Amino acid sequence: ETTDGVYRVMTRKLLGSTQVGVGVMQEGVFHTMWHVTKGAALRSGEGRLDPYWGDVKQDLVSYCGPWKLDAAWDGLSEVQLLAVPPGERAKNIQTLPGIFKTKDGDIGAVALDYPAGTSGSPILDKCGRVIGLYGNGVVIKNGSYVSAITQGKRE
Amino acid sequence: DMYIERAGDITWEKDAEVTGNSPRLDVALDESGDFSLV
Ligand SMILES: *C(=O)[C@H](CCCNC(=N)N)NC(=O)[C@H](CCCCN)NC(C)=O
């Protein structure tokens, strides 16, 4: 299978079938977060998906080709987390992103909480383009979870 | 071994639920790709 869309990342090494994360297939390239797969190869039916590009600091990794997703949050409008939680069906959820202010620049952040297994879920703009992936952030002075909108650099 | 299975299309849903704040946070990014609050 190679169809564009959102996928679950499953494993059988633990009890039953466990979902470790989510990813985006686009233009024949699978995109997920690095800590989901640790960079290991993946199976898509009878076929093999091999890592092609990876960076632990960005916490991104692509399979079968270079990172294709090149849309970015505009900083103004709201976005949708296409959350794909383990055991449950894909649900769009809409948010206005906040902002991670870092020494190297500011990046969007979505203040939505979902179990691990949802790491790698795509964040979308009103036009449908994937502007980043969910699952790498901080925990705030309360105890809830704020993920960055993690996006890669296309070629 | 990890395997992938499809869970949907990438599409904006026009009648989606709206939730979540828009907080502004100061963060550092270590060499391990871990965010932390400053
Ligand atoms: C996916 O593995 C999860 C997505 C958020 C689940 N946490 C929550 N609902 N509190 N990602 C993580 O848990 C992050 C682990 C990967 C860290 C990357 N170096 N942890 C954080 C703090 O984002």
Image (cartoon, coloured by chain):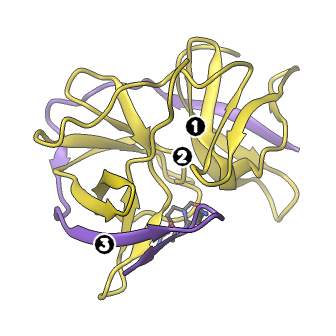
Chain colours: A yellow, B purple
Which sits in the foreground, A46 or A122?
A: A122
Q: Quadrant of ligand 1?
A: bottom right
Which residue is drawn at the image coordinates 10% and 41% (left, top)?
A76
Real-space CA distance between mark 3 and mark 2, rounded to the nearest whole angstrom: 23 Å
Element type where label 3 sits in the image: strand
Q: Does ligand 1 reach within 8 Å of label 1's beta carbon? A: no
Eyeballing the image, is A53 above or below B2?
A: above
Report x, y in % for residue A63.
Answer: 72, 27
- Amino acid at the residue labelled 2: Gly
Q: Chain of mark 2?
A: A
Which residue is drawn at the image coordinates 48% and 44% (left, top)?
A121
Q: Decide: few, some or many residues near mark 1? Use Cα within 10 Å; few <14, some 14-19, many ≥20.
A: many
Mark 1 and mark 2 lie on one chain; the one further toward the N terminus is 1
Report x, y in % for residue B38.
Answer: 36, 81
Q: Decide: few, some or many residues near mark 3? Use Cα within 10 Å; few <14, some 14-19, many ≥20.
A: some
- Amino acid at the residue labelled 3: Asp
Q: Which mark is residue A75?
A: none
The residue at which mark 3 appears reads as: B26
Q: Which mark is residue A23?
A: 1
Which residue is drawn at the image coordinates 50% and 59% (left, top)?
A136
Locate the N terminus of chain A by quadrant: top right
Query: Is mark 1 in CB contact (under 8 Å) with mark 2?
Result: yes
